[PDB]
Image (cartoon, rainbow over all chains, first blue to last red; front, side, top):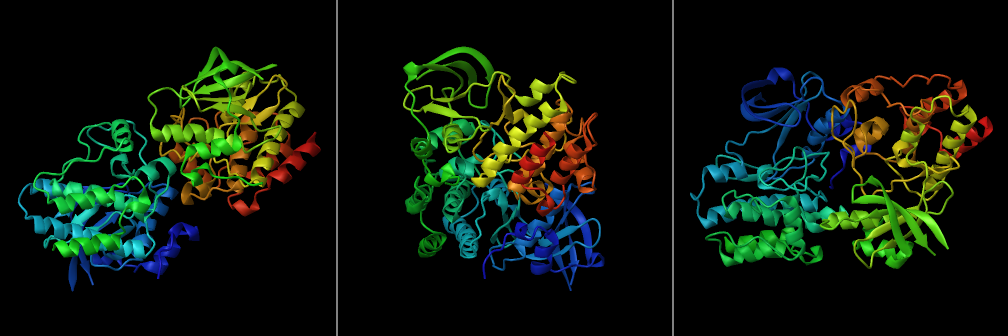
Length: 286
Length: 286
């Protein structure tokens, strides 16, 4: 089995039919708002199937056709995957309004926010375990020939047992354009700070460029959610990186872990480890 | 011969070495500023070879590596082409700073601004002649398997003899995101208003999506530079087009010319005419 790009059908319902389960709206109840996303509100609710807690993404009325395509495209991508460290798609409501994407609920939310909330409270082994889980998910994706393009701690979700799962499967994504962003970068866009040099310059996204992003995720984890490159503008970030600058070792980070970050940030992508190497390396440490 | 993506080299100098002529700085003199570009100022000047008038684009100091890639990429694309209706690249200055792209000078500037307020000054035959020139350049590009993605009257240049030539060869341009844009599109990006439905929804850009854009260019020409869809928001433009709306016939436009626009705007790309058809159809109007 291998990844299929839902765009190839030129009908978003195709990937939905092929890779998702249609859920009847009588089985879904929303209980609270847990966020705002690109397409509309995001809720926590319950899915009757027995009932299970779920995250519920909705498509706000008045959407464009491109939005409708991108919305269903997210489900058409996620539904192709089945792995412990990849957010599980429960299903979609496509045949009623508003349309919904129903995924497994993750109690602790996004990883960057979670580690900030819990700054300093974990052991190295716990942090490494979070990184191993992310890497296992990315290994599964790379073997499916899926390149994520937008791997960052804000796109990893954390459950009550601290299991980390890759989320945010966007059909659409393009690189942000802003030369600055000293505090915050764009919306819907891939941030320059997490993206490999060849992906920025040559638009060359491969699993090796996901590895670069994973290195940045390692640094976010080991720093408890520090912003990569602090308040440097994107202009200065790219200049420094191409001159050989790499983020310094986080406080209390084992040298073996920082060395793996540095391997992930090899300027020349062929010299970076693959996700399989990373999982093995992190397994030895655990 | 067929189009070569400069990105394949992962070295912007390779397309430059392959497809352009290195010009010595002592052969170029700038005389006046004729515009501001994405990369720096644009000048009119002279090129010593004899001397010929040239447009001169400069890469302003302080550029990012991506900008350097995109700048040299413009030349690396344009140098692969040789046709009466495609802006000629005289050469580049890459070995010295500031770097320069040197092209043939076009006295009358951009087509959309040239036509504005000239209502009644040209005969239908002259306007059709302009459209036939553009179509011939596009026929040439399509045969080279180059999809332009950004065909619009603002990207067509006009010389003193009213010859129209396709310009604006950008590396990896992206579609604008903006749901509004009633008066304008901020620049740099491919405007929604000129883009075929399948390229917006599914990111499917082909020569047939260039044909959609060409139909929009036909309307800009026959309206003497009116803004397509007036001051509708991009949101409302996409909604209308997907509901079957098409721009109305321009005042004084012969029906055969409007019929051709309408063929270019077939919802299904496979029903649109090819550029080689468009050239022949226009030829028979003249």
